[PDB]
Amino acid sequence: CSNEKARDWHRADVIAGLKKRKLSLSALSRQFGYAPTTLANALERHWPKGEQIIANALETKPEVIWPSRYQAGE
């Protein structure tokens, strides 16, 4: 019924995976300035630039945390 964690990283695979080192949507938010609400709402809101902030911490690409949303190829 609820896809919640459809194919992308669970809301917990995001924070649990990231927080596994030293990251929390609350810290990355004030580290750049955007209130904690912005970073959080960046999970379902229209703002692909918010995922860059998170993926940047893993030195990876957002296409790795949300692959089923990106499929136009490369």
Image (cartoon, rainbow, N blue to C red):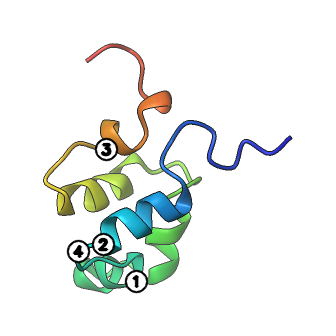
Residue 20 position (above or below residue 11): below
Residue type of the residue flagged with mark 4:
Arg
| SS state under label 2 | loop
Residue 35 position (above or below residue 50): below
Cβ atoms under marks 4 and 3 closer than 8 Å: no
Residue located beneath label 2 in the image: 20
Residue located beneath label 1 in the image: 26
| SS state under label 3 | helix
Distance in Å between CA atoms under marks 2 and 1: 15 Å
Q: Earlier in the sequence, mark 4 or mark 3?
A: 4
Q: Quadrant of residue 2?
A: top right
Q: What residue is shown at x 26% (from left), y 54% (from top)?
A: 55
Disc 4 residue crowd, few under 14, some 14–19, many 20+, Cα 10 Å? few
Residue 9 located left or right of residue 19: right
Which mark's residue is nearer the viewer, 2 or 1? Answer: 2
Residue type of the residue flagged with mark 1:
Ser
Cβ atoms under marks 3 and 2 closer than 8 Å: no
Cβ atoms under marks 4 and 1 closer than 8 Å: no
Residue located beneath label 4 in the image: 21
